[PDB]
Image (cartoon, coloured by chain):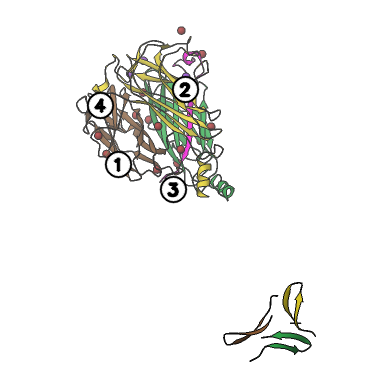
Chain colours: A yellow, B green, C brown
Amino acid sequence: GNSGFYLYNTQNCVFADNTVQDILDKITTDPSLGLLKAFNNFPITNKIQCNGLFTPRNIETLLGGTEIGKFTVTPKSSGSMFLVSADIIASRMEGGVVLALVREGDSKPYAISYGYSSGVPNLCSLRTRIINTGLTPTTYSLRVGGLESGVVWVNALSNGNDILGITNTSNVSFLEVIP
Amino acid sequence: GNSGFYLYNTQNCVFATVQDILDKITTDPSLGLLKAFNNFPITNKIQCNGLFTPRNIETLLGGTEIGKFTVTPKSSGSMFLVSADIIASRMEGGVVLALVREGDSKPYAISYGYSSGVPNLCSLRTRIINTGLTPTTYSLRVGGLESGVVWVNALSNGNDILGITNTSNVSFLEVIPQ
Amino acid sequence: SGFYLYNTQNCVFADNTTDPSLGLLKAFNNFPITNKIQCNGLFTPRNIETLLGGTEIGKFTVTPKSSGSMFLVSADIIASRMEGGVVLALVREGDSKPYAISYGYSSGVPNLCSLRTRIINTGLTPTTYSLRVGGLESGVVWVNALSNGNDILGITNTSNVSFLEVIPQ
Ligand SMILES: [Br-]
Ligand SMILES: [Br-]
Ligand SMILES: [Br-]
Ligand SMILES: [Br-]
Ligand SMILES: [Br-]
Ligand SMILES: [Br-]
Ligand SMILES: [Br-]
Ligand SMILES: [Br-]
Ligand SMILES: [Br-]
Ligand SMILES: [Br-]
Ligand SMILES: [Br-]
Ligand SMILES: [Br-]
Ligand SMILES: [Br-]
Ligand SMILES: [Br-]
Ligand SMILES: [K+]
Ligand SMILES: [K+]
Ligand SMILES: [K+]
């Protein structure tokens, strides 16, 4: 109940009362998923004279036959295998052909197979499976020679000449599979 | 029309998801991402006295059994791609191979090979149509074409080839048709 | 401080499963060949790099499901001929010579003659291939039959050509 104007020090004042990509990277790089599988095919087109023999004395060493190819492969999944197919065009005077797949570091062949030529070229095959031991590149080589005796030519007639006058192709394929 | 001060009642106032897919993908048989593989090595030497003839080719009695294999598909509506790669010798002549599915009364698939006397690879390549996800058994029989004795994994006299044990293989790879 | 007029008014104042690019998705096709075919066409140095060598025994159409894929091809043909060489050639439609050539053998009795290769796919479109078989230089070759054209073991036999899609490294 009071109102008006008044001085406060020096002021005159009024006053008053008022996710797809994320899978994709996993899938293409996670080795533990059994998805995803390496494949490699290795053509062999050169004519190779295989003078090295296979015999009981060298069959369990590295010295049997003649090397015709060397292959490096890498698994993309853990605990996998490679299903291996070697299909080699070979000729020899009537007799047996031996094939040996060797894994680098071992002291003898990983797998041995047998083929035949009558004198004219014939496919000689090795089919096997490799047990992979990690995700590291691994190198394998294929050797080919006569069974006990004879010279074997790969990709050529028994004298070394071109079959049918052309270059021919033998193949070694590796297909990764999960057991 | 006014300014000043006034009383109002008593007041004086102024105014103026990844794991969820991954479990599916790694276990669902209907998607077709899961593919079985099995390889069966055969390393024993087996004398195959049983023959294949027109009278026994469509029975279970042709040739001699060299292996029996049990496999399980992981996907529905799948097939197995089969490769049997058998080392065999015989005196000059033909070799017959027959894959039999358990329960059937004759071979599923038949193939042919050759030996001149020295060992040679004899193969059978086929595809099997799978009918569920249950283990299934198959067997491989080998014998002469019409006549002759066939040795598997051995020379024509039963001895070791090159003095070692040799390996024949039968592989089954699961694949999905289109 | 006080009150004053500002204009008219009186105022207070104061100071305060379908993506091809992955690639899961792998086609498989198998083509059984069960007819007996008398392959009178020969392979010679003069026809080996043409379309005319041998005799066609099958034609296959396949479709890749993934990009930058290959088909792993296996042709496993039952064949007989009087003592000698068998030649197989896989041809891709539109080419003017074989994509791959392989060799087999018969002594007179049937034997498996194989061709194993890989094909490089170039898209996701159906593509047609064919297989041709014939003698090496001379001789008649019978597919799925004895060297005289009769049934082997008195039954129908089956040769196969398979295509399996795979993805290279
Ligand atoms: Br490749
Ligand atoms: Br020796
Ligand atoms: Br052969
Ligand atoms: Br296995
Ligand atoms: Br009979
Ligand atoms: Br059985
Ligand atoms: Br049946
Ligand atoms: Br022995
Ligand atoms: Br199919
Ligand atoms: Br047909
Ligand atoms: Br064509
Ligand atoms: Br061309
Ligand atoms: Br017969
Ligand atoms: Br694959
Ligand atoms: K021989
Ligand atoms: K090596
Ligand atoms: K012969």
Q: Amino acid at mark 1?
A: Thr
Frontmost of labels 4 and 1 is 1
Q: Which residues are magenta?
A: B149-178
Q: Residues within 10 Å of mark 2 (few under 14, many from 20)?
A: some
Q: Does the closest atom of ligand 11 sit within 8 Å of the Cβ of label 1?
A: yes
The lab-note entry on whether marks 4 and 2 share a chain reads: no
**The residue marked by circle 4 belongs to what chain?**
C
Q: Residues within 10 Å of mark 3 (few under 14, many from 20)?
A: few
Q: Amino acid at mark 4?
A: Gly
Q: Give the Cα distance between marks 1 and 3.
A: 23 Å
**The residue marked by circle 2 belongs to what chain?**
A
Residue B24 highlighted magenta (yes or no)? no
Picture quarter with ligand 11: top left
The disc, 4 or 3, on the residue closer to the chain's N-terminal end is 3
- Side of C9 where C61 appears, left or right: left
Q: Residues within 10 Å of mark 1 (few under 14, many from 20)?
A: some
Q: Residue at x 39, y 39 (%)?
A: C69
Q: Give the Cα distance between marks 4 and 2.
A: 35 Å
Residue at image mark 3: C19
